[PDB]
Length: 237
Image (tube, rainbow, N blue to C red; front, side, top):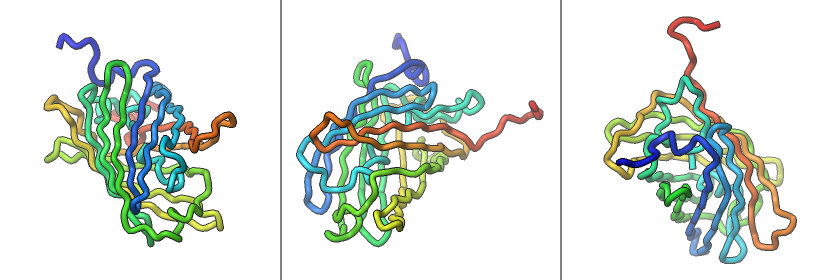
């Protein structure tokens, strides 16, 4: 240290990403691997995910939030509020509980850190109390995704952040499956991190398929921008 790059300096170009998830939902075990790249300058993520154990036992859209918030575009005036990059390269742990309304829940733990040049997201997911004939195990969700805001606040006692948001998944009959997300992030290292003022991230996501791919898979294009803090002191405009 004598470490060439630290914090936000690691994200000035395109960074390769590797995602590994091991899952168990109501005793259906599965694994997912993902590869792609992130460009934090534009808040852009491009990834392809493959279920390596056969058919995915839950709908792909239910895994989007779980499957690297480091790649969010933070405006210059908000750079001091970017907890995610400030925790790099040593990384952070992200913990979630995701409540599917009138159905089961996911509990997840992810370690996000660099291994050399590659940003790695290693996840374990446990799902319980799902209805075998409900929207999730019954595969009744559309293969699509809506835009959402994700709300971030500092948790000074844990030297981390707390995050909450609700996802609305479209059901094939025109209705909505809600998924309430509760999230906390904690740094792995003992170094200083940036603890943000209240703000949010705005997500857009597009799901597609690789026409040449026979394995069960999802192609994801996603844009993420921080917002909710304005540039005043004096009124610039």
